[PDB]
Image (cartoon, rainbow, N blue to C red):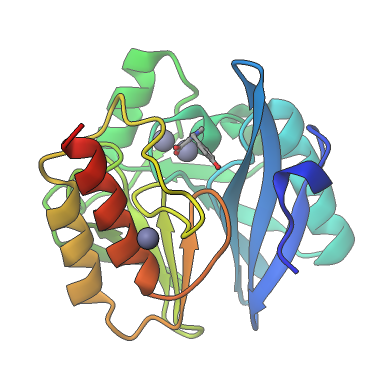
Length: 231
Ligand SMILES: O=C(O)c1nccn1Cc1ccc(O)cc1
Ligand SMILES: [Zn+2]
Ligand SMILES: [Zn+2]
Ligand SMILES: [Zn+2]
């Protein structure tokens, strides 16, 4: 069973194997009195690991590295942050001090610097235009267009048919929008459409928060976004 927020003390990290050589990591963080679960991804690349997104803070990200060594035992050599918010880049300095090469799009690096969030060291080129895709080792990176944020990327694992949608995709159990201060409401459903059209073969779909599912998370997200648009 997939872990939920009441099962994870803030400061601890769970791993959940999705497929051969593909895990999610789950952590929790408090914000404005409430506690929120958050996902990232781990993809085996030969005898090293590619990390997708931090565990939302320095403390959680150190625990993330320790759980990975405990349960997997392979080195995390590169990390990709899928947008500039703290649940994606919070902990980047911990990754760098551990010798992880940290990556993000120029768009994400630029926004992180303006917000005051931690800044991934390396730039991911070739992703500035909606529909752009580039290979990054064992995954494909895809920029669907602005949605939850103007810079959000999605990540696809072709060997396992795992689509990591990040925060542009909502879990089915989430029926209201949430933190859309930085969203492009007008373009969000169009960007989701681009994800559908580019990865129709996806078997598993991982949201940035909550329970994985299939491609029906995409239509669900469109519904929730349109309802918030019509407030
Ligand atoms: O929406 C987001 O992307 C986000 N990032 C940090 C906090 N949130 C809001 C949230 C709301 C409900 C949840 O189950 C989980 C998260
Ligand atoms: Zn976000
Ligand atoms: Zn988020
Ligand atoms: Zn729904």
